[PDB]
Image (cartoon, rainbow over all chains, first blue to last red; front, side, top):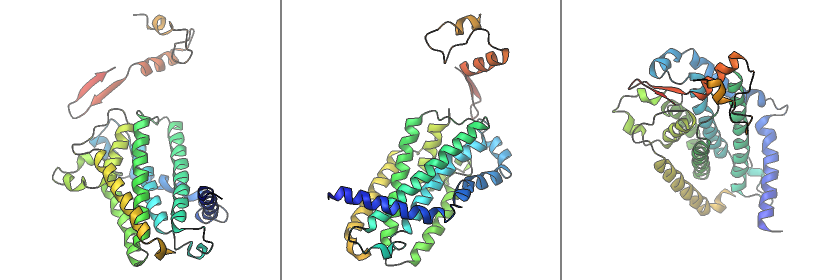
Length: 255
Length: 49
């Protein structure tokens, strides 16, 4: 058969295998992932609701939090699940058609589908409660989301390839996902950060992508100086090229 | 200004026109939809579209 058809069949089989383990034997995971963002939002309604209203009263926490949480959750899920690949299918590398890239690709499709479903459900239930839920500039939001998808998949592939020799360095990477949630401006608006602290944070492309997504979502949402799309786009492109080339280098070591 | 007469003029589309004989609450919601007010807090400027 053609190589494309073989790759497509392998990806479909890997997706079918991965869905059962990711979700659960009784699919109890849907009771968690759907409850995944809500458990985060509610406590922040009891922490900085009045502080956020003092900071910016134009928008509301139930929508501001959602506009930055699920994209960050989906980036984090992409990175984590793609990093744990290869090893979890190490016994399946015995059929000459299952290559290490296919596992991370299939996990990427699964995570993207799950998080897109979560986004749709969250927007539907936010519009059910009367909150503002329709994006203003949908095309720009889709473009920024695609850039975030590419950056997350690139980082996941790079970390999966580079951690093959050193498994322990994998674990701290997961730990390194925790501070980003606190420094990407997801929980609180970054306009309150003191000016001498922002230029160090400008090197984080996830912050730029979250800010641009929020700007494309809300009507009249301001963007701080130094926030652009060119820097995250170049970072994602360079990281993806390097990750693909490194996987090409160690194509046989993983197998 | 007879807003009710004006907003019911275009019969071409049934989605963005004020149908005849509608409730007062629906009229208020339609008016709130067709008049957007935003406030810029840092300068405190009110923009009306």
